Length: 56
Length: 191
Image 1 (tube, rainbow over the protein chains, first blue to last red):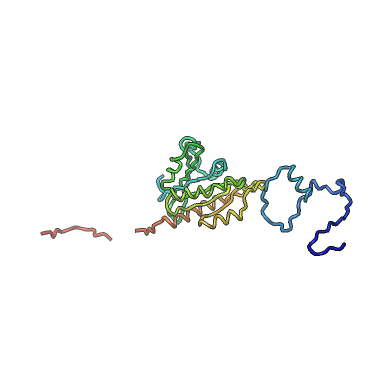
Image 2 (cartoon, one colour):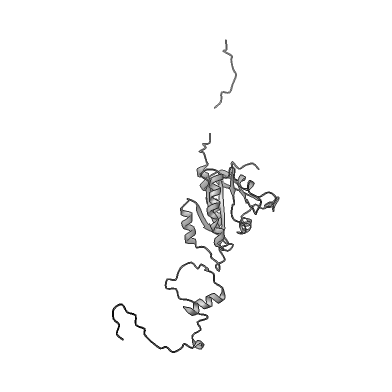
C-alpha cells in the first residue's frame, strides 16, 4: 500500500477472535521486568483489577 | 531506690490509631497505675539502664489527643529531651502527619532534641502503603534515626532505644571525674 508524504492512509488487517476458554486473562499477574522491589499495595478493587489485567 | 544519676524525659509522640499503645506495651516496667491516657493525656513507662557506670532512668510519656486536647498536649513538651515519632506502614495518612509532628516538636520542645522514628507493625506485608526507601530518605534530611518493628522481628526497637539513650547521653553528659591526715596531740600557737 503506497502512502504519499503527510497523508494518512487507513489500513485493514483482520484478526481471529481470541477464545477465552484457553487464555485465562482474568487470573494472570502482570509481568514485572525488574523484579526485586518492595511490594506496595497500590489499591484496586477486584472489578477494576480484573478489567485492567484483561485490557493489558 | 534512688540510684539513677540522670532522668531523661522522652515523648512517644505519634498519630492516633497507629498501634503505639501496643508498641510500648512490649518494652515496659509495667506496674502501678495504667490506662491513664484518657485521664489527662499521658501514660508512663520507665526503665533504668547502665551506661559506663552512670545509671540512667528513662520516662516514656505517651501523649495522645483526640479532639479536645489542644494546649496541654503541647505544654507536655516543656522540657522533653527525646522523641520517638511513631508511624505505621499501613496507610499514607499516618506518614503524612510526620512533617507537622516534627514541626510542632521542634517549635515547642527543647532546642536540638534527639528524635527517632519507628514504624510499627511491619509484619503485615499485604498493605505496605509507604516504602522503606522513601522513609529512609526522609530520615536523612533531619539527622534522626529510623527503624521498623514487628512482633516477630524482635530486639530491633530495644537496640534502637538503647542506642538513642546512649546518643542523648553524649550530648547532655557534662564530663564528671571521680574527685594522710595529721593524727596526734596538738599545741596552740595562736597569739
